[PDB]
Image: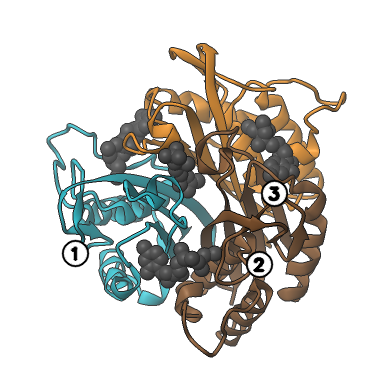
Chain colours: A brown, B orange, C cyan
Amino acid sequence: AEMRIGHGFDVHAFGGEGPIIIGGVRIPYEKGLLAHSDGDVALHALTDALLGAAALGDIGKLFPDTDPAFKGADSRELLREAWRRIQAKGYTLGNVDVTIIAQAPKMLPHIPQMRVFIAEDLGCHMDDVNVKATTTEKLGFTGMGLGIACEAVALLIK
Amino acid sequence: AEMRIGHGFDVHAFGGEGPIIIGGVRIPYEKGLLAHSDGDVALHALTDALLGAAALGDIGKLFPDTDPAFKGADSRELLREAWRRIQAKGYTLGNVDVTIIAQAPKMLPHIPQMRVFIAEDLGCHMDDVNVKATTTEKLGFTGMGLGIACEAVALLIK
Amino acid sequence: AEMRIGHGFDVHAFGGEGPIIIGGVRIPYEKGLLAHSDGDVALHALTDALLGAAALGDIGKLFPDTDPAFKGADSRELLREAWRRIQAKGYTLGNVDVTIIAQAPKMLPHIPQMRVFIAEDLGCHMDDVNVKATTTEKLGFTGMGLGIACEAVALLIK
Ligand SMILES: Nc1ccn([C@@H]2O[C@H](COP(=O)(O)OP(=O)(O)O)[C@@H](O)[C@H]2O)c(=O)n1
Ligand SMILES: Nc1ccn([C@@H]2O[C@H](COP(=O)(O)OP(=O)(O)O)[C@@H](O)[C@H]2O)c(=O)n1
Ligand SMILES: Nc1ccn([C@@H]2O[C@H](COP(=O)(O)OP(=O)(O)O)[C@@H](O)[C@H]2O)c(=O)n1
Ligand SMILES: CC(C)=CCC/C(C)=C/COP(=O)(O)OP(=O)(O)O
Ligand SMILES: [Mn+2]
Ligand SMILES: [Mn+2]
Ligand SMILES: [Mn+2]
Ligand SMILES: [Zn+2]
Ligand SMILES: [Zn+2]
Ligand SMILES: [Zn+2]
């Protein structure tokens, strides 16, 4: 059994009306997130971490910012699709860990539901999906409420 | 033997008198770090990386920002406590890698002592604990001396 | 077979004439990168991820900012040298995943060539090297075109 590591990172800016979608979960907030998809940084970062582990590039590589094939869709579809590909190459999920970086809104109440979504989307047990949040103690663009960042790592098995 | 990956990230802002505690080590600096605990970003980030690998959430989940149980303590206690929990679920340490992001102070002289602390706190050999530092070449909130960031990754074995 | 995780992170600021070197690849851009070496954030971050996995510190530890031994060289040499050391301790490459964080230039056309370089430098198959890019949607120092950040993770086998 060969094992593979992956990393992902994403940022999206605030704009317009709430809510925001993070980890599939619709979360109420004063601002919404500017996006060409649904702006779900958590799932984008996770997808990159997963793809990178399977050495398949990134989301922008699999789903061009323009292309007809998979266009203007919600990030859960993109996640499921990438996982389809990652499995086609003969990988199963080791586990994933996600780190949301945001000053607000409060993510912790929504994390259990995010895990239901991700566990479903990758067809695994919840105990292989972990999600956290942190603030930057009001420092930097996230700390000064301009956007949200997210990091994810992934482990795969062949 | 099943293997598990984890990631952690933390930021704290400068304020008041030095010194700062980073990786358990008390380091002299003009400013100190604003915190509800001892503001040890290195250990916080490590703890999250470890917890995330064991799919146990984050420090804020285990030790609420308010709660009586483990209150206003130093981050080495929180680290040891989380490791107690991570072991209770039947995990041993693969290895940890930590990345301090700070313009100053200079971290490199203190890294050997940080590793003594962490290796003790997780009850392992030093050769399973790695710590680095980097500046952001004067860019961003860390680069403009407003705070310190840290990243950690962890590998666990069941 | 024991397995080891590593993480790396690097930033460099824009300045002077293009081009920039990223992942060994010379990429045309209006500004160049301020550096004591060639300012290759991608390879620096990768090297730290690799060294950290082998618990050998960071690049600044192996190659002091001043030292005669390996001085003012290009980052591919530093990468190859660190890999020599990492192998001397009895490690082979599991895989690496790299994440470039930059508003511009566009990295995606250059990624295939970056992988040729890294795969050569670590003497492995391309399918063990993954590289991505992302913008911070115009937010933060990278988003406001002041510099480039990069993250890397690495897996090693003993
Ligand atoms: N400096 C950069 C940044 C991104 N990219 C590519 O552009 C894509 C999308 O960039 P983005 O930062 O807007 O990512 P999204 O969160 O919008 O999907 C990435 O997935 C990469 O393929 C690039 O080629 N060079
Ligand atoms: N956007 C956010 C940020 C943090 N959190 C939670 O709040 C806790 C503490 O946040 P923090 O950024 O002040 O972390 P500390 O370094 O102060 O421990 C985290 O551990 C999460 O449980 C959240 O629910 N939503
Ligand atoms: N706060 C810090 C930052 C960096 N360092 C050390 O200084 C070295 C170089 O720092 P740097 O941010 O300029 O890294 P480069 O990208 O210039 O190689 C690091 O590799 C660390 O060894 C430190 O001791 N304390
Ligand atoms: C964990 C990672 C990837 C850290 C990199 C730091 C980063 C992207 C800072 C954003 O700039 P900023 O918020 O400091 O911009 P400014 O302070 O200029 O508003
Ligand atoms: Mn806090
Ligand atoms: Mn430097
Ligand atoms: Mn975008
Ligand atoms: Zn995105
Ligand atoms: Zn903290
Ligand atoms: Zn560098």
Taking the spot 63% from the left edge, 79% from the top edge, the residue there is A73
A12 lies above or below A76: above
- At mark 3, the secondary structure is strand
Describe residue B21's horizontal placement relative to residue A114 as left or right. Answer: left
Are the residues under marks 2 and 3 on the same chain?
A: yes
- Pointer 1 and pointer 2: residues touching (CB < 8 Å)? no
The three-letter code of the residue at mark 1 reads Pro
Bin the neighbour count of mark 3 within 10 Å (Cα to Cα): few under 14, some 14-19, many 20 and up: many
Q: Position of residue C52 (x, y in %)?
A: 43, 46
Which chain is disc 1 placed on? C
Q: What number is the disc on residue A65?
A: none
CA distance separating discs 2 and 3 = 18 Å
Left/right placement of residue C114 relative to residue A141 reads left
**Ligand 10 occupies quarter:** top left
Q: Residues within 10 Å of mark 1 (few under 14, many from 20)?
A: some
Residue C28: assigned label: 1
Residue at the disc numbered 3: A132
Q: Where is residue B54 drawn, in percent x and y? A: 72, 51
